[PDB]
Length: 278
Ligand SMILES: [Mg+2]
Image 1 (tube, rainbow, N blue to C red):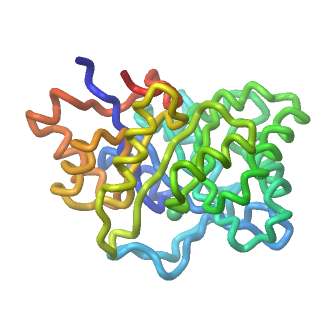
Image 2: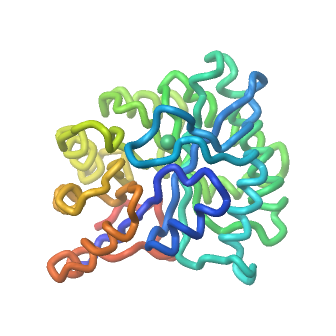
Image 3: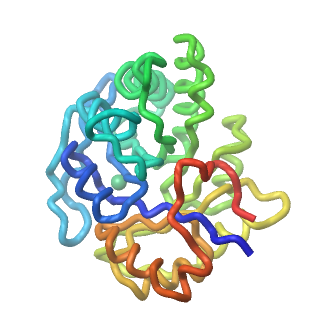
C-alpha cells in the first residue's frame, strides 16, 4: 500500500542557527526545549547538563528570539524559508513549576507563540506544533493554551497544534490524562530515552498497537533519540511515524535504502500530522 510519511526530527534544536543545520541534514521537523521562569513564562530554549551523548547541552536563546527564527524558517517568501520544515515539538520543561502553574504556563506559551511565531495572524509561520508535556498532572496546560488563543481571537490556530506526554507513562494512564483534558485528536506519543542509555521496543509496540486499533487515541508515534542505522531500521520496522535524532543524515540514508524507500517517505506539509496513517 501507500508509503507511511515519516517525520525525521532534529533533537535539541535550541539555537536559531541549528534550525538550518538540522534541516539541511535532512530533518523535516525539530524538537526544542522550553524553560520557564518562576512566573510560568517561557524563558529560554535551554536544556542544560546532562544531555545526550556527543551534544553540547548549553546552546540557547531567549524563547521569543527562537520563535522569530523559527517563524522566518517556516514562512513562505522569507529569505530563510525551509519548505521541508513542517513540525516543531516543544519539550516544555514544566518540572520547574508548581503543579498549579501548569494552566498559567499554557496561557503564557500561547501569548508568545501568537505574538512571535504566528505574528497575530499576519503571515505567520506555517509549521504544525506539538506541545509536549513531561508530567501527566500538568494536563491543565492544554486548556490554558487553548483558552488564551480563544481570548486573543485566534481559536483556529488550534488546528495547527497537537499534544504529547513525554514521561513514558503507561499508555492507559496517558489516555486517562487526555480524557481529563477533554482532548480527542491531534495526539502524538513519544517513547524514548537518551542516546546514552539502552532501550527496547516494548512501549513503542504498545503505543503503535493503540494507534492502529479501532478505538485507540494515538495518531502518531515517535521514538527518541536514535543515532544508529540499526536502531532506525528497528523503529521503522515497528511502524513508528517519527524518529528523533542527533543525525538526520543517518536517518535519511536508511530511508533511502531500497527496501525502506518502498515503505516510507519523508513527510511534507500536505501530510497532516494529526491523521493516523492507513
Ligand atoms: Mg528535550
